[PDB]
Image (cartoon, rainbow over all chains, first blue to last red; front, top):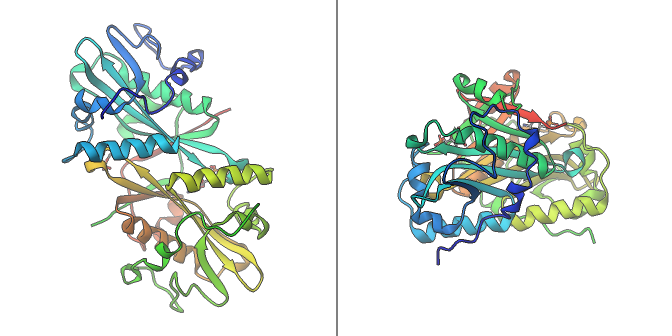
Length: 182
Length: 182
Ligand SMILES: N[C@@H]1[C@@H](O)[C@H](O)[C@@H](COP(=O)(O)O)O[C@@H]1O
Ligand SMILES: N[C@@H]1[C@@H](O)[C@H](O)[C@@H](COP(=O)(O)O)O[C@@H]1O
């Protein structure tokens, strides 16, 4: 039952106004031309057998996941309309090489506005030098703007701030706080 | 058509294990006994006529909101299962006096785990001294733990860190970054 149906409408990524990109690419790549033998598209359940968790596990721990577990989560994300899990496939190898999620959050403030979040971004190690993290960040940042978000946020270590400033992000005055449940 | 149907199941707030509360209350209040003539419950569309935006507008700007706008947003939040917009009503006055949102975010990492977020917390000014922000933070923090989140996060100004440490939050090493779209 893992199939090729995308989590969200793929034309949203073609429709992204790439003239609004501010990151430097050499060579020039775009969501429509992401690089030699690469496709930038929404996640589908079939990516479970294209090494999706192999990419993700490079960011943090993915643990033990059943197929039914993965598909239950995928379906909930699709149904909400709020999740934009975006992958890069090397179509020569039939393998995911990069992933990133845009989450939309609906509010009542600012005249019932929407905000974006960048989550779970990781590029497979053997793809260093393919500019995919840059492409994913720029694409998703511009996607949220396309989806009428008033702002988009993310978290990173101070050492990596410079990277995100290139897509228009600045350091907030607010502290990021967290509680991990035991 | 604005009615009394809660955004989420209200028994979730009664079912919150309040023995796990770590905030200091004097007098002792709980989600079940939030204070004289107060009820702690999910938001319903009828709260539009109970001064919900009057409370919210004290946190930030709410702008101009149509009834149809408010109900479209409410319904999307209810449908996703991911939004826990929680209010305090003074039932003597028939008015909202406090609000806070728990957002659930579904991931694939950590064996398809869930994370919480605390958003849009505000207590009406005339309710200073009723311990409602403390009650809301503790309640929602414990609610996310109940809903099987592995962690919960929020953002605040450094000046306000001490307040949130009381519910188990610590300052992250990661910087909060933001882009506001023009
Ligand atoms: N910005 C990313 C998050 O999107 C990701 O979820 C997190 C994983 O870390 P953890 O495994 O501690 O939740 O790392 C970074 O902070
Ligand atoms: N933690 C709260 C957020 O939950 C809220 O959404 C924000 C509103 O600020 P703005 O109006 O700049 O989005 O204020 C704080 O940062």
